Image (cartoon, rainbow, N blue to C red):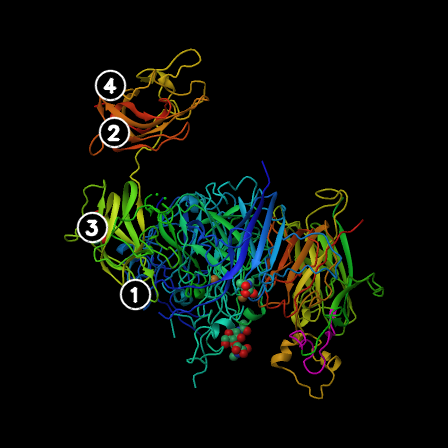
Amino acid sequence: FQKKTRHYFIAAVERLWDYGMSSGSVPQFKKVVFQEFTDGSFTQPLYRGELNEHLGLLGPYIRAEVEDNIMVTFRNQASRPYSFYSSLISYEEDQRQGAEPRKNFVKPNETKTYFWKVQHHMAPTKDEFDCKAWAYFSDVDLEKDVHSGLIGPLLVCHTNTLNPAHGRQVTVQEFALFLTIFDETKSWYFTENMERNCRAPCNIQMEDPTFKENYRFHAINGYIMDTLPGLVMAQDQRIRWYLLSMGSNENIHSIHFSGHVFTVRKKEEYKMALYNLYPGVFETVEMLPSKAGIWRVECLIGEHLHAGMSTLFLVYSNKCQTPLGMASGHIRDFQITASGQYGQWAPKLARLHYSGSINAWSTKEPFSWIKVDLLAPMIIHGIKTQGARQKFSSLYISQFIIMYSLDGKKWQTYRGNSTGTLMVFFGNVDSSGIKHNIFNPPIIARYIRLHPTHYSIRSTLRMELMGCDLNSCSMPLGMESKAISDAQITASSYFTNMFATWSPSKARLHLQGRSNAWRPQVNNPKEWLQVDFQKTMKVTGVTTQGVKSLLTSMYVKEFLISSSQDGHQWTLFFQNGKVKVFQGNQDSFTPVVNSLDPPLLTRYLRIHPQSWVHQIALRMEVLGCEAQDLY
Amino acid sequence: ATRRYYLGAVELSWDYVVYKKTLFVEFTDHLFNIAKPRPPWMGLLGPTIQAEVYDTVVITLKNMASHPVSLHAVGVSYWKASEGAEYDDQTSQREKEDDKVFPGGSHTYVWQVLKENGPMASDPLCLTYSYLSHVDLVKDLNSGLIGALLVCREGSLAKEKTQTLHKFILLFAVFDEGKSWHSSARAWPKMHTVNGYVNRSLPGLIGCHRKSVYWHVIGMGTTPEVHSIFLEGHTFLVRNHRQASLEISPITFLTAQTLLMDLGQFLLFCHISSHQHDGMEAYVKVDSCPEEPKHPKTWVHYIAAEEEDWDYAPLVLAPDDRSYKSQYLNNGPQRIGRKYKKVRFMAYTDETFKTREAIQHESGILGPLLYGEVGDTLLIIFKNQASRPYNIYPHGITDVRPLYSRRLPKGVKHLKDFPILPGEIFKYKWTVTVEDGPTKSDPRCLTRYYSSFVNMERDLASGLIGPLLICYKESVDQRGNQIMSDKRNVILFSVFDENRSWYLTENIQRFLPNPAGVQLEDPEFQASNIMHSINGYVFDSLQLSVCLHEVAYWYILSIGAQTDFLSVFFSGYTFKHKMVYEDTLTLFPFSGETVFMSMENPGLWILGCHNSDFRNRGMTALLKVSSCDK
Ligand SMILES: *[C@@H]1O[C@H](CO)[C@@H](O[C@@H]2O[C@H](CO)[C@@H](O)[C@H](O)[C@H]2NC(C)=O)[C@H](O)[C@H]1NC(C)=O
Ligand SMILES: *[C@H]1O[C@H](CO)[C@@H](O)[C@H](O)[C@H]1NC(C)=O
Ligand SMILES: *[C@H]1O[C@H](CO)[C@@H](O)[C@H](O)[C@H]1NC(C)=O
Ligand SMILES: [Ca+2]
Ligand SMILES: [Cu+2]
Ligand SMILES: [Cu+2]
């Protein structure tokens, strides 16, 4: 096991503070932020990924293990020169100096690069959590350069907790939360008061009841209207929260998550419902959000809530009603086929809460619709629907009907309990109208279409889906555990000599050896492999794989299946038309989630290889359980 | 089991002749019929509702008010068909009706405790949680909607049918009748106080004497408004992390316990200057009982209270009208590096109070470093050598009695009362027992202090401060006593408000040139003497010498600088307080806390505090680090 020197090419820039949701006179603001770049040539802006856009109006994650190396090659791009600073900023030694100028000052366009061993000083402990949380900010003016906008998160981890995949994730999913109450008597704000809001209609309110951030700013980042974006999480994969309050001396914030509870470590771990964040106290706390649906975080402090903390988070993942995954789903799943167009396109990006200007679905089309392949027959209990925000335009969909297909071929409309002819659904009312519709009787589908019945400026949408699975026996039938005896499987024929016996009794999803899989005596498509269940079974699908023969690769590319009740005559598998051309392997290893449209009820299952790689070679497994026994 | 609580919410008229609200009723209704548990400690309180780990509670609220009012929990799980919190959680038609009970409505409530929200393996037997109401969070609260809601392991109905427990719910709460449901002319709205028991008001009951009493304490308000609560006996549950004084903020609840001595209804503070006048109080009648039908050290201190002069900023000075610092000291003519006449504790060699005790020019104003492990006895022999009379009392120990007798100075109710005039000396005995020292959890040395108590700060502010250290047992045995235990060192965060000092206008005939315009009571001059400092030293005045690879404990406290709290700094350095590692210490005005530090970051470091509105009003020092020798 190794140590790593992990640099982070990072800088400081500006743009700032948007509101446009639903709740147009909106103001420009021009505060400073940290920003992660791509290399020394400070060019690639390093697009903030869907996985960390919650971070939003503060800086990128900087992360390390115990016996590690942290490095920051930093460029300032601004007016007032700023700097990097946190606690373990372990400077070094001494110098021929004049009372030790240890002053960190980073002038615009200059590059101040610093890097240091991260001792067990900064590390979390055996008593603690898998990772502790620390702040970095500009120390040029720690007072102003915090309302200005140089808040930053820093994570320090136990050894063997991160990945090749960057960051960690061993049942993780982390989020930071940055609760301040920003104010502009701080940082260059002069270049805002008479930069915008004033021309020849000016000279109105100097510092009398004007309070422009105690007119607004109650941060949970600075996407902190009463709604910030990226709080996507799986209703299990237990989520760690990084709460760090900052600001001034009224900046106590007491946060909680409705209908959820979390555990905090210290001496031990004791269970808590809300946490008085203090300024300078960098909390880590974890929870297991086993209640599906759509919630929020709020600083419970009366007057704070009532000017910006009611800031949503969504859980999708099962019991049963979780978000079906639109934050936690499928990067660019499914969309339409002509219905939907406006440069800033359709889905691709039409999810709930998706922050930005290029955000959601968008079509000035009297005849429209969008389509989600749930990639499996699913229960859909409801649909949270919301709208977007334009130039100064409020635009959304006001009315909609919902059609679904369980199959793809023949569709039809919907008729939520005893309505009339057709189930008319009520849309949004603004650019943040999360109007969680529920399906009165539920819906079982694979595909859902949404069709507008009236729009604002454009048929315009962003949405999540409510529900969860039916729960078929997606559990290994006994090929792996070998609950199915070596006796219990024959094949069409087996290859055999002296240095090998590739008998059918070897076809096992992961099996090592000299002869570690099934092989036919020669290579024919009308060749097969047969499982015999000593009883009557129900099947989801067969997991296929090839063999690593130390010789060459061997695997099966395409196959067929056949079923029987008698075990001597065979009714084979079909699509909605001809036989099922099965999408099989491509390597010595790697298995295949290959399942069946009509769950096959049988007792005699036969594999029918069609196309292969070098020889026909099979390590495999069946998924399922059983209905009644034989009759 | 499966528990039901059929109780709605009402409008009621309140008192102790000023102010009438909306409360949270208690009653056995199907309609509107009386039903009361409330007599004692229950103030404005929806009934303390208790459910165990595996249970399922059903509140059904009947609303009666001009108010649209909700019901919403914390610390518990439920379906989006409760929550009781309006905002677009998508929620179908019937899933939002829990969110706001339209005025004079009626709604059922679906409440669950799962395993995942029961209390953790080792902590409070029973968790502190409250039940709120939020439609208009600010309104619903200040008005008067709040109750206690408790949750704990498999056995209340069964192991409190057979168990004995002395438990109350104290609701430390700050309703503001200007933020009520409610809206020439001279007398605008007000309140600020415990359980709803105002000013000095007192509630009800007590617990038995020879054992322990548990209180689920719920923090309240509609603003960032911190308190700091006390009474006699230590208040040792936080975890079994073992605390000087319950310290409550915005919205706070964890749950704590204490022991007892006898009948003395013990005094119940909010103990801060600002909250005081309009503050919180209640008694505690600790009575007799129903249910019966390498040894220990001996320390010595000769300390005198004694008048001297204090230059807060000697080393460094550079004023004119050139700064906010330039303004400090005597706002008439005199205004350079700032000199006042103070009275600080100072210890002598022996009864012959003659031999000057060599000083610790790092502790500045601070008294001699007092220390005593559990089991020891402090014989503290104390002379006044300042005219205007004072005394000595340690916030920490409870067994403090005059040396030889168990008398009370001929007349007074207890020593922190009146005693010691100019000249006269008193022999005090401080005996320290396990109860006032640390534990198998804390550090090994909790931080405390001694003030004088003839006047409170009209004393203290004038210089009466010194650090008291109570500690775990050890001597060439126990833990860490094989080559050396590296020395003890104290920082004191203190605003001295000369404006109150028992040397008030004494000091104006002094340093200030001419009272030929004897001006007093002023906007800027009052601000001109509020001295935000660490050990009297201010504005990077005498810092501290240390070196790298050196390692020892810091003991720190907030005193005199009140009305507020202190998040505290240390540039680039990090400490192990509470056996975690944090970089900033949050400190109240009781605030005794004890950190530990590996000194190995060479350079100037600007120790101050994480609040950047005093560290400009002074309130900063420096620290230096560089290799040593030995
Ligand atoms: C209890 O509350 C009453 C409320 O009036 C306090 O009475 C006055 O408070 C004003 C504050 O503006 C002070 O100027 C006076 O000291 C009080 N005057 C009267 C008429 O008594 C009162 O201070 C409170 N009691 C306590 C605990 O001191
Ligand atoms: C370099 O950065 C700062 C940003 O304010 C500025 O002084 C200067 O104009 C920049 N250099 C360029 C783009 O020529
Ligand atoms: C629609 O019918 C279902 C059938 O049980 C019912 O549960 C639901 O309450 C009805 N929808 C309404 C009136 O909200
Ligand atoms: Ca609801
Ligand atoms: Cu807050
Ligand atoms: Cu108070």
Position of B601 with respect to A141 (left or right) is right
Local SS, label 4: loop
How packed is label 1: few (under 14 Cα within 10 Å), some, or many (20 or more)? some
Q: Are marks 4 and 3 in contact (CB under 8 Å)?
A: no
Separation of residues labelled 1 and 2 (CA atoms):
57 Å
Asked if the residue at tag 1 contacts the one at tag 4, i.e. Cβ–Cβ closer than 8 Å, the answer is: no
Q: Is residue B102 left or right of B462 when viewed as pictured?
A: left
Q: CA distance from mark 4 to mark 1?
A: 71 Å
Label 3 close to label 1 by CB (< 8 Å): no
The amino acid type of the residue labelled 4 equals: Gly
Would you name the residue on which mark 2 appears?
A: A600
| Residue B271 relative to residue B9: left or right | right
Q: Earlier in the sequence, mark 4 or mark 3?
A: 3
State which quadrant residue A548 falls in. Answer: top left
> Label 3, on which residue?
A416
Query: Gap between marks 2 and 4, in whole Å?
Result: 15 Å
Cβ at disc 3 under 8 Å from ligand 3: yes
Count numbered badges in the picture.
4
Q: CA distance from mark 3 to mark 2?
A: 31 Å
Highlighted range, magenta:
B322-343
* Mark pair 3, 1: CA separation: 31 Å
Residue on which disc 4 sits: A567
Chain assignment, label 4:
A
Q: Is residue A512 magenta?
A: no
The kind of residue on which mark 1 rests is Pro
